Image 1 (spheres, rainbow, N blue to C red):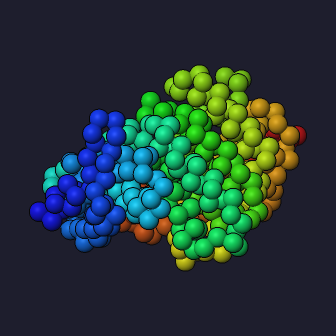
Image 2 (image 1 turned 120 degrees about the horizontal axis):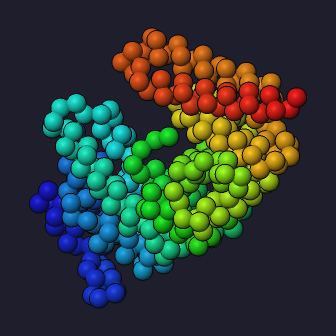
Length: 345
């Protein structure tokens, strides 16, 4: 706290449009990570750093201007991933007391501010360049530090798109920065590549969050975001269906079935099935582009999930509202299957 404020002033400063580090910068960044790992139940550390606007005043300048210092750039990414964590995941559940509730809402206020700071083509430019380079390396020729940095970049993009909650202009600005930086092309590459199946859950979360404000029939152009953002999303969705959906949805489902222990969030799969099958159908694309989720096996899988959610809503009563939300996403996916099959007669 006094330690915390001394560490923050030992990062650097901006002389005009230029950021000057201090020689103990990498050290200070890592100290801030240690503080965040020892914070109380108030999440005081991330609240203090949020109040101080360290992410904006220091970390983003370091990221954009000093990205050739490899250990420091990696340290800053780690810190930003932790600082951009969804507020639900920081406090666990929603505070009912007027105390923790003021905290939760302060954490969320800082998340919303980080989301607007990231509205910048140079931030995403640096992330996309770095990701591009990391992926040029063959899959079995890059080190665990390389895969670990891929993972953190994807988690950071995920977290920034997630703000403020689970499944207007700020998100739109992020989408445009994703488009202008080329990160859109890296996401499509990752989705369509058998060799990058380890990243498929991360990529599906990012793609689903990119489309969160959108209506699939409207986007398909047979009847909110600015027109040039909607056109970019239409183009992205078209390419995604043409080249990526079957592969990505097949790999996600594989992870979901093989890694039950990890309690992956399978709501992104349910959300994506309903959105992208609705778009494919509205656009009159060929059925083959959604064949992976248009099958008896998919009916069975959605039915299994809907049964499980419904049973949990009735037995895990302390979380009944969360299970009801999951049940609603599964049901919407089932309705889209039924609507698609019913138009095949």
